[PDB]
Image (cartoon, rainbow, N blue to C red; front, top):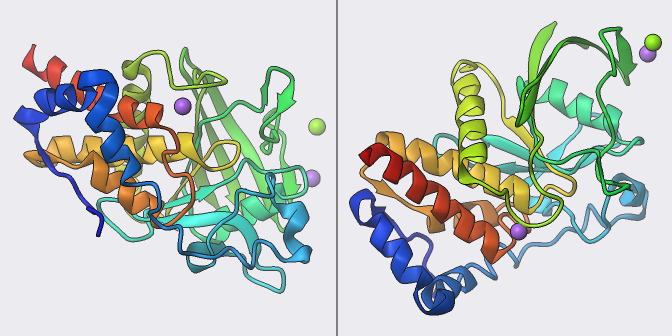
Length: 284
Ligand SMILES: [Mg+2]
Ligand code: NA
Ligand code: NA
């Protein structure tokens, strides 16, 4: 019944987006609403097992059984999902912000899945409410996380993001961690340029890690902000390699694999604004 893709010629995108925004977002809202039920036929029965309750930050934001990531051993559960990219079916893992009680699980996943790049698009605390544990070391001294030892080699705090490098050893690898630090507590970032430049930076590093497993992306719940980051990564790659861009199809594909991947119309609009602004700047 529903469209799975809405490709737009790059030179028609500005006017396409204007058409969507016309009349108080009349058509934009219609297109966005077509995505509403994507993926929603899937269950989350494993995440709901009593043994797993304490492992979910939010008891109503859970991975689908079909696409969840499994930890080795006899407690396999983590609140994390495999997500496709432009390039590969399991190009990302989306997860919640680790809890104090699940940070060892998070690091275990990072080790087992051969992760080399982690993207974080939440603060640990937002207006005094905890959103994510500070699940990495505070300084350069080593610490265990479960059966792994981790050392933070460097921490570089820049105006809109912070980049850390960790050395990890389990049963040695360098991991980079990209922490975007200007996402407002509510709504979308206040400029397009900030997130565009952050995504470009991360994508540069991912491209230099051709051996790596999935890129991990998280916010507090692993929901809209994470979906918006991944959708933007996918769409900007399209702008660099193709004559068409398919924001609708990117969001559709993400929603097939985890709930709330791009979760507000505002985020959907923001993705279109980013693409618009990239194309406008080109024409400089
Ligand atoms: Mg110490
Ligand atoms: Na330790
Ligand atoms: Na929003």
